Amino acid sequence: TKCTLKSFTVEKGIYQTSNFRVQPTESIVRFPNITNLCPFGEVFNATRF
Amino acid sequence: QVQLLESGGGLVQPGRSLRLSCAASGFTFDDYAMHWVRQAPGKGLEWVSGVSWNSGTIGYADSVKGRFTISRDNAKNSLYLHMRSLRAEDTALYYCAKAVEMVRGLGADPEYGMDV
Image 1 (cartoon, chains in turn purple, cyan):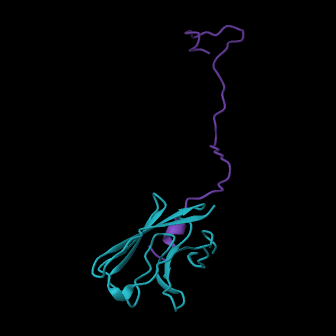
Image 2 (tube, rainbow over the protein chains, first blue to last red):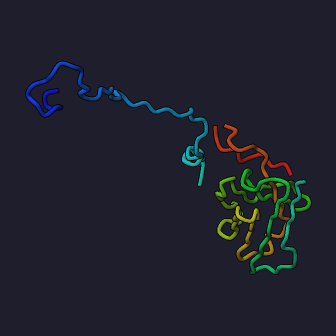
Image 3 (cartoon, each protein chain N blue to C red):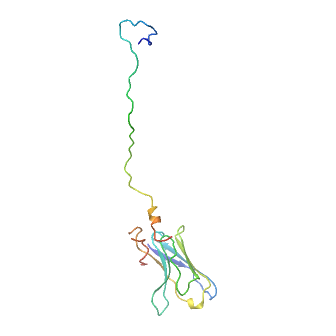
């Protein structure tokens, strides 16, 4: 408050100083489950080429 | 409707080449292995060649090794069978046949069972 008023003597009252704010602590990512797949295992396990 | 169109009719003399074409209707070409089976009169069916669903040639016959050749055409749903330097002893009737087994039928690749 002293450096908010640019003064060395603070007079009786209530002085708005600053802002309070909570910070995000962790990161959450979500997606629907995976069901289909690409047919690579159908080629690499095939009997012949 | 499953229609087999076989093309390449004509007369050929021994010492030259030959070419037959298989066309299929009513089903997907890539899903089944395509085989060639021949049968001369007065004799039973006998495998002559084949090729898997993956268009992989399976080999050549014991009698005609080195001259026959087989190929697929997955783009136009067609099939080529070429006869290099035929001889008069190879005279018979050629037959085109399709497999049945649905793809990924589990423990080897489904490539057998000619039906049509």
